[PDB]
Image 1 (cartoon, each protein chain N blue to C red):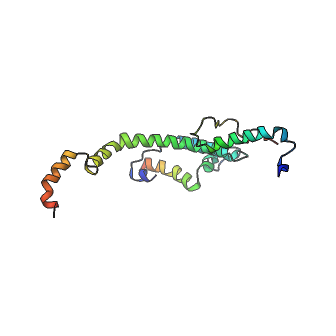
Image 2 (image 1 turned 90 degrees about the horizontal axis):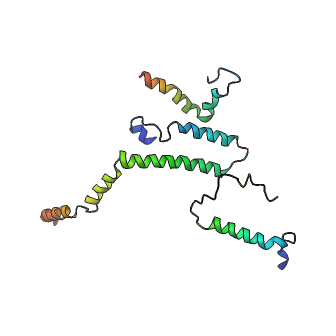
Image 3 (image 1 turned 120 degrees about the vertical axis):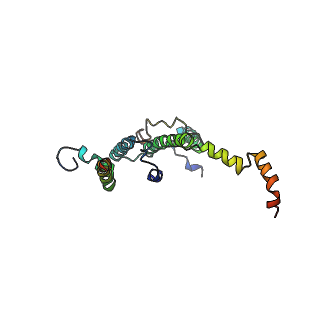
Length: 50
Length: 96
Length: 36
């Protein structure tokens, strides 16, 4: 149902989808252990989206 | 540990750094959140150190290359002229 | 050290890093091995 679009995210829903797709690709592409998994800012130390 | 049971008291590959990794694990225990990333990083560092020391022991101390060369010469018939001469000499015994 | 002070914290640092059997082994056999 077209109604499944989140209205508050709808203006940014496309960018959100693109970011999610890129991250899903990177984690889903068998990347060599890319140094860009920096041991620095943990996603737990990253302020959560909330 | 199994090799050090038979090998003379050669210390750990990491030797005194084992306690350092223990201290890192204690810090991880002190971490309020379990991070798989930091644990995996420490485990990978220890693994890499152990693997490099093991490779050095195997190749220089344990001469893995010599054993592979022997296996090639005999099991893989690497000494093809030698195994050919052996076949030529033993054919009467091994044809039966 | 083990359990012989109060404020001291290193006295148990090995006891938290190492298990009691392994700690006891390390603590006893090294001088034991030296004397043997």
